[PDB]
Every structure is written in structure tokens, then in C-alpha cells.
Image 1 (spheres, each protein chain N blue to C red):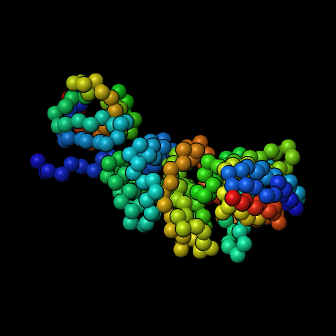
Image 2 (image 1 turned 135 degrees about the horizontal axis):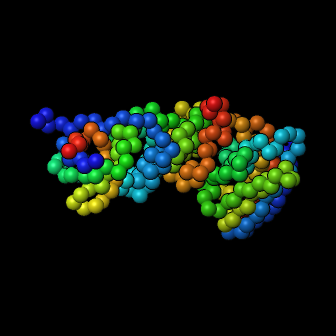
Image 3 (image 1 turned 90 degrees about the vertical axis):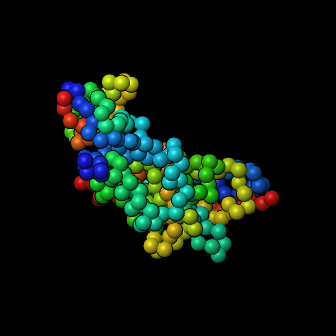
Length: 114
Length: 56
Length: 117
């Protein structure tokens, strides 16, 4: 299982920190990612943290978001700064294998207002 | 190993030594076919295409 | 007296040449943000062939969809969707994007270790 938490109501310009606890499933040799899905729209890749702890981010997410992992707990986090209404979405964690996303959780709701 | 340039070589890259036909250079390193050289005139160093030069 | 200078000596791309050339283009602002195309990359690869002698067989990227990472460790550009984001990777429009971390992190090899044996 992949169970994310941290979601809530945020004012424009505010911050939020998301967290995922991962079960199964060999974690340490897994590339991990956070994605998000707005209503009606298509899921959008947001951040990636690689097996050897290397990171990458979408454009819309810049120098605002930060993805990190902690190997002792089978856990991955997403720090989100300077939030905007268009960041509103359900955010979920996933395992990336090659070009595809192997596993993914149901996610946690982030709602940003102004 | 002193060498002279058979042709002009202009490179936009900082790691290369640009030169003109005639310019003499000292070879510091025969590292394949791209050699590290130093210009006698300016003392600037850089890589050079070995087929652009001939031994003296 | 033949007035054309010879082709500079030929050689295969290395980590360090890719790093060096990536950084040159970064300083010049040469590729950043440019929409990728087969022809543009060919001009890029042939310019490196002509000026430096590298066989133009090195500038390959992971298959996507989404960001395409360089197979050649040392090359510090990746291709990023500019109209994100599609299911068919062949329909995604990409731009070159410099990424300093690609000098230290072989992203392609971590996502696609099968390419490396």
C-alpha cells in the first residue's frame, strides 16, 4: 500500500508538507514520485526522487516544491511552498519504473484559496 | 617536440588553443590525435588537432 | 594549396567532453528553451562533429513520455515537455533544458538500467 497524508485547506502563498508511508514492496530499490490530479484534468507529474536520492521537478513547481526520502521508514515527503490556487489537486505518491508508474496511492487533497 | 601549424585553427572553446598557419607550439601531451600544446609566442595552452601541425 | 582545412580528428564522445560542451552552451545560452526537432539536434551534433571531431551517435535520450534524460552521462541537457502532458510520447513537444545535476546524477541509468550492461 501507499498512503499519503498532509492535505488540507491553504491560503494562497501558504505552505504544506506531504508525507507517504509505503508498504509491500522493496522500497530502497524504488524510484519514487509525487503526482497530482485536478478535477476533470489529467494527472500531472510533480516531483521525482531517484533510487540514489537524486531529484527532479515539473516546471510549474520550480523552486517551490522539495521532494525528499527517508530510507529507514519506507517514507517519502513533499514540501510545498508559495502555494497557488492552481496547485489545488489530489496529490499522490507513486513508484516509477522505467517510463511508467508502477504503484500509486489514493492521495491526499490539497485545496488552495485566495 | 616543437611543431608548426599547417593551417589556421580557430576554436570557440576555452580548452582549445587557437592558432594561425606558421605559429610554432610545444607539445606537452601526445594524448591521441588531439594533443595538449603551448604557443611559443603567447604561452597560452590548449588542445589542438594534430593533423593541423607538422614536426620540426 | 587546397584551400579547405582538413576534418579535425575523429573520436567517440566521453563524459568529460559532454560535460565541457554542455557547460559552454550553457554559458552562451545556446540551447536553453529551444523547441527540440530532429533537424535542430542534427545541426547541433554536426557542429560538434565539425569543430571537435565527435561522431554524432551520442546525443540520445530516454523514451518518455515526459522528461527525456540523456543516455550519455555528462551531457547536462534534458528534453522537457513544453505543452505537458501527453500519453503518446511522439506527440509531446519538447524543449532543451539545462540541468546542472546531470553532471553528478546519471538519471537515465537509474530509470533505465537495462540500457547499461
